[PDB]
Amino acid sequence: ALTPKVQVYSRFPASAGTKNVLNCFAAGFHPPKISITLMKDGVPMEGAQYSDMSFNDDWTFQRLVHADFTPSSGSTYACKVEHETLKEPQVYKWDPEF
Amino acid sequence: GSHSLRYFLTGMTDPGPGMPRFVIVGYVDDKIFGTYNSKSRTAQPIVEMLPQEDQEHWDTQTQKAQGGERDFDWNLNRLPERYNKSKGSHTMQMMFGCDILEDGSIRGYDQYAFDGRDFLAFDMDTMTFTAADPVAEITKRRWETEGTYAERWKHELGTVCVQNLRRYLEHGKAALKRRVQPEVRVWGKEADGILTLSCHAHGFYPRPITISWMKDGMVRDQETRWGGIVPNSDGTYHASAAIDVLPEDGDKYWCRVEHASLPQPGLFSW
Ligand SMILES: CCCCCCCCCCCCCC(=O)NCC(=O)O
Ligand SMILES: [Cl-]
């Protein structure tokens, strides 16, 4: 492929109203330029941090984006990914499992 | 008792808004210990892993890094034209390091990639190069004929690297020996006729973990799919497996997780 492969997960087992961290991991892509945005209800989350560019042993690039959040039972959390291999941004929905 | 030090170096002509052109990430046993990038132009430890580093060590590291950034700049400038593909963005990568195996023998790794594709590699134990293709061969023959790189990198891989690994394992021993159990959550959701059971392991160290699914005491590899092992921001890891089940059989399925932090594998239901 060479497009991003994207996984969205929380640092801890998620629970409504308990402070946590939402992670968006994108991997397997090339070139390394890439846009990853964490979002609540389609609003970008504040305070997001981005890992130093690194790559897998197959040379494919990867990046972790994370941000503090307190999951809300009535919110949709998503990760939006733009990459030159994609014609339109792809969004990936967090599955809260709670 | 096997331990590893790895440097992952990227040079980029198009890193993206607010992003460095040249990045070095250093890992010991799957923990980031230090970083360099062209914006900071400094090499710096992860203070969580390396709480009491001397400035002397990281001055040396910072200067070797800056030298590495120059060399990548020189590659990114010559290689595209040599490969008759000067159009586009371009990347340069290097992976190198060493292993100290449980018996004390050493292994060196030294590999390069241009535009995400194998370019060149060097084997410390024979001090010979290999090229990925006829254009890389030009680089290989120039370097081995000049004689200097092989001495350099034999020394770098088999001495300097080995010394720094030994140092980082000692300095970071508080962080390296602390075993961190996975926190496991099993969860199903029923759509149409099927129920998706997902088993997620949260925040474990060290990085190797196994996850598998069970009906009775029989595994069910055929219907399982694994998300793979992915990082957290704090030097732990995340892993997951999923399986689809008839919704009237979900209490019969158990998630099994093996990890160095668990004397016995752990069994988790929905
Ligand atoms: C974790 C931050 C500390 C970084 C450690 C410094 C190690 C960087 C190694 C220099 C890379 C040199 C590239 C190269 O291959 N140049 C060509 C040549 O050596 O002739
Ligand atoms: Cl339960």
Image: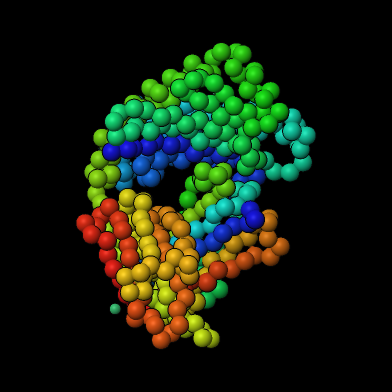
Q: Which of the two residues, B162 or A19, is positioned nearer the viewer here?
A: B162
Q: Mark yes or no: residue B60 visible.
A: no
Residue B177 makes an appearance in the image: yes
**Where does the C terminus of chain A fall, quadrant-wise?**
bottom left
Question: Is B184 above or below relative to B148?
Answer: below
Q: Is residue B125 left or right of residue B148?
A: left
User: Could you tell me which quadrant the N terminus of chain A lies in?
Assistant: bottom right
Position of residue A83 measured from the top left corner of the image (x, y, whole percent): 64, 57
Image coloring type: rainbow
Residue B71 placement, left or right of B269: right
Residue A73 is situated, as x and y percent measured from the top left of the image, at 41, 81
- How many marks the image carries: the answer is 0
Image quadrant where residue B239 sits: bottom left
Which residue appears at 71% of the width and 28% of the height?
Answer: B134
Report x, y in % for residue B59: 40, 28
Q: Residue at x 53, y 51 (%)?
A: A62
- Residue under the image location 51 percent in, 53 percent down: A63
Q: Viewed as shown, does residue B163 lie left or right of B109?
A: left
Q: In front here: B198 or B18?
A: B198
In percent of the image, x 35 and y 55: which residue is there? B209
In the rendered view, does B235 fall on the left or right side of B192? left
The answer to which image quadrant residue B112 occupies is top right
Q: Nearer the viewer, residue B35 or B115?
A: B115
Is the residue A68 above or below the residue B180 in the image?
Answer: below
Above or below — where is B87 with respect to A21? above
